[PDB]
Amino acid sequence: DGDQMISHRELWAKIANSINDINEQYLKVYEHAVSSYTQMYQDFSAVLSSLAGWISPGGNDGNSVKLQVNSLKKALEELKEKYKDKPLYPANNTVSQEQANKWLTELGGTIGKVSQKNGGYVVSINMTPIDNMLKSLDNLGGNGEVVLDNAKYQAWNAGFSAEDETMKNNLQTLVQKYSNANSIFDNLVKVLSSTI
Amino acid sequence: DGDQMISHRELWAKIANSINDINEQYLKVYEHAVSSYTQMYQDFSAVLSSLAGWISPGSVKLQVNSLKKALEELKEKYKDKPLYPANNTVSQEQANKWLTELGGTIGKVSQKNGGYVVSINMTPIDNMLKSLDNLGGNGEVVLDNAKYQAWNAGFSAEDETMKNNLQTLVQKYSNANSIFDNLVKVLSST
């Protein structure tokens, strides 16, 4: 109904109510999701740095690689256990199942995963790239340091860097979605100051 | 002021005026800048599609004068085909607003007259012309195999910058439509 009148003063408060609702239920949700994933990937970036001390030349001739997988497996698993309790959304407590499912679609099923903490749910960080690394590590043969000829170190590192490339692509699109979310908020502010 | 009454009908009109303004002043500006830069690179493929015939054994010999006549023609065709605005000029303050939005790597603020435009940054085309210079030669050059790889690597690096310059603009434009789409959605039903 277009005849419904509203004061300029009532309109200012309704705008400030909608803006605050958006920043609280959309902007700050997107920012913390980006926040949690960079810090997750930053800790994984610390394991790639420590990977240098876990790979040295080995073998009879010396062309091969001697990767201590137990040290690398230990670091990737501690990274998993660190972020079981650090979800993308929400930042505090839990929310309903459909609220966790609504923000799973908005963020992406690849980046996040809906989990129940008993009663309430969260959108936890999807650790599929890390878990894919661990089982490929688990299949390398032996339960310790493995001598990897350049042909089969070629195959493992190609898949290891791919799961690393996945988390970067995941972080890139999460950063881009937050960039557009801030731009939608910015435009939504200018469109409403247009009324006065 | 604060006590003046407004109808829901008047609010719809003030919002439709802004969505129209955003389409004319933001989306269609992106649509033209993407197209104008796309036409240039598609024309740059000329010096590219002719590179194979301009290379032959000598060592390696390269027709630099032909490789240079075509690049200097590419700058002439887009000397006055700017990225923003599509027509006439704008303010310099208005032009710098879009130079930052599109990045100083693809745009370049120029003073056409009293007004300003954001022209296409032909620095990669300039970069290749200056290294085609340093090669020397009467009009055709014969190069050591070590330069031809050194030169062809840096030349293809300038083409790779224009390729990444284009798709970066293509994704910035597609994200602009994504912002406009969701901007209407939350406004269509707040």
Image (cartoon, coloured by chain):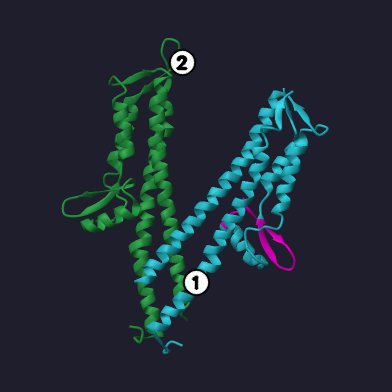
Chain colours: A green, B cyan
Q: How many marks?
A: 2
Q: Residue at x 68, y 47 (%)?
A: B123
Q: Residues within 10 Å of mark 2 (few under 14, many from 20)?
A: few
The residue lying furthest to the right in this view is: B138
Amino acid type, residue under disc 1 in the picture = Asn
Do marks 2 and 1 share a subunit? Answer: no
Q: Residues within 10 Å of mark 1 (few under 14, many from 20)?
A: few
Nearest-to-viewer mark from 2 and 1: 1
Counting from the top left corner in percent of width and height, residue A78 is at 30, 36
Horizontal side of B69 relative to A95 (left or right) equals right
In the image, which disc is placed on residue B20?
A: 1
B142 relative to A88, above or below: above
Q: Residue at x 64, y 41 (%)?
A: B158
B144 relative to A42, above or below: above
- Chain identifier of the residue bearing label 2 in the image: A
Q: Are marks 2 and 1 in contact (CB under 8 Å)?
A: no
Q: Secondary structure at mark 2?
A: loop
Residue placed most toward the observer, B28 or A87: B28
Where are the magenta residues, as a range?
Answer: B102-119
Q: Is residue A180 magenta?
A: no
Q: Residue at x 37, y 71 (%)?
A: B188
In the image, which disc is placed on residue A44?
A: none
A92 relative to A72, above or below: below
* Distance from the alpha carbon under mark 2 to that under mark 1: 65 Å
Q: Is residue B104 magenta?
A: yes
